[PDB]
Length: 49
Length: 49
Image 1 (cartoon, each protein chain N blue to C red):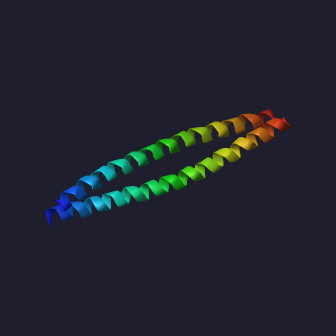
Image 2 (cartoon, rainbow over the protein chains, first blue to last red):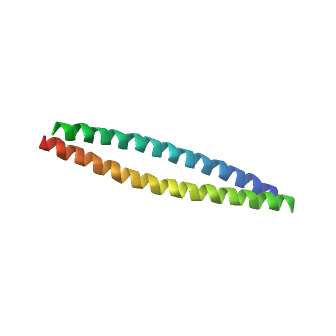
Image 3 (tube, chains in turn cyan, orange):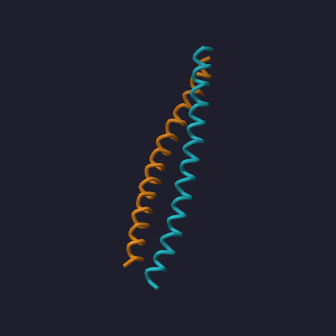
């Protein structure tokens, strides 16, 4: 009974930490998009100046 | 014994995912700082032009 209860809690914890790492990857992709936005306006603006 | 073996396998799995999310958080902070630095440098060149 103790082993199966530990297995169930462990699986739920695994699913929670999987969801957290997926959210962190999504935030990384959004930050990459923001970084690229900043870079191209750097390039436009250096040409302008 | 079988339930204990499954328990330690999922222990290793959750430890791997935890190391992954720590690396993702570190990269997240590293990218956020670069995004903010680029942003205020945008503002600086735009004042110049």
